[PDB]
Image (cartoon, rainbow, N blue to C red; front, side):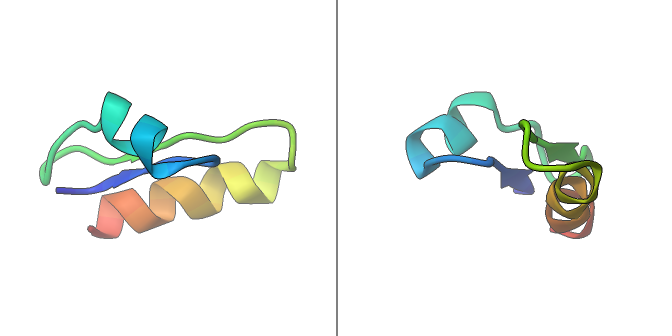
Length: 44
């Protein structure tokens, strides 16, 4: 189960995806962050 969110846990699981899929919820923090997120899921 690889699901990350750039806010809270309630929203993190709200979207989710799966152990086979990788999702990285980003915002207006920076391009780097948008990548770090997907990095935590893609690996999860």
